[PDB]
Image (spheres, rainbow, N blue to C red):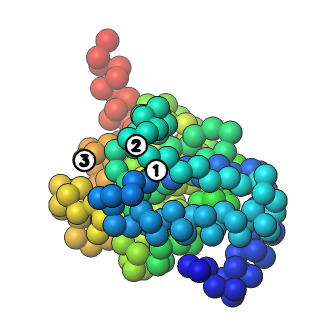
Amino acid sequence: MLLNLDVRMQLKELAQKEFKEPVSIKLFSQAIGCESCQTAEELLKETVEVIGEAVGQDKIKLDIYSPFTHKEETEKYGVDRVPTIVIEGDKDYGIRYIGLPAGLEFTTLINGIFHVSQRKPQLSEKTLELLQVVDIPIEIWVFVTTSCGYCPSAAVMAWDFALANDYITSKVIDASENQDLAEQFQVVGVPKIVINKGVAEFVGAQPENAFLGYIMAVYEKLKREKEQAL
């Protein structure tokens, strides 16, 4: 098992106290040409069964798709790499994990599930008040690794921002598994955050208000470009 009795006991308690609304998890995976996929399928099944047993089989479900077969699902969630994990509820908040959320990123996965289950992001009222103005699609990528010590914090923060706004999409991308993307954005130290594929970037975990700041700076520029273009 990827989750020993101790971790299961822990996740079970965690779920019972933290879990609320039903959660949907969609894993896009492929048998050949993807090294971490099999492990991702295994980790997610165990996670879902553990949580499902703790709060109810109907509170959480895992769908595993293959881009080759599930063209519709793949297209809908903008999946182009595997494994890609979608955490959502009634709606798609643009929360994605590209790669295996193992190591220190496992809590990222767990916290993503819980935050989504709670239909509530862990962002101050100040942040949420200011963020609601964002109404132009903003994409957030957080490059991480399973051992990166500050990534979990950055990854969950990006996911919360996505959960807080219907125009924000946040993808936590394992830099080891997506070296091509990593290189393309000169990812060396992690976490490295990239907004709108290069419009802006910053390194390391960020105080919530600074992370908001980047998003808002990117948004204001997109806003005026949207206005001037009239």
**Relative to 87, residue 114 above or below:** below
- First in residue order: circle 1 vs circle 3: 1
What's the mark number on residue 198? 3
User: Label 1 amino acid?
Assistant: Phe
Q: Which residue is mark 1?
A: 28
Percent position of residue 212, x then y = 47, 52
Residue positioned 57% across, 64% down in the render: 44
Query: For the residue carrying disc 3, how many other residues have a C-alpha within 10 Å: few (<14), some (14-19), or many (20+)?
Result: few
Mark 1, Cα crowd under 10 Å, few <14 / some 14-19 / many 20+, is many
Percent position of residue 25, x then y: 60, 52
Dot 3 falls on a residue whose secondary structure is helix
Looking at the picture, tell me which residue is in the foreground, 222 or 66: 66
Q: Which residue is mark 2?
A: 67
What is the secondary structure assignment of the residue under circle 2?
A: loop
Dot 2: within a 10 Å radius of its alpha carbon, few (fewer than 14), some, or many (20 or more) residues?
Answer: some
How far apart are the two marked residues, 1 and 2, measured between alpha carbons? 7 Å
Residue 6 locus on image (x, y percent) = 69, 87
| Kind of residue at disc 3 | Gly
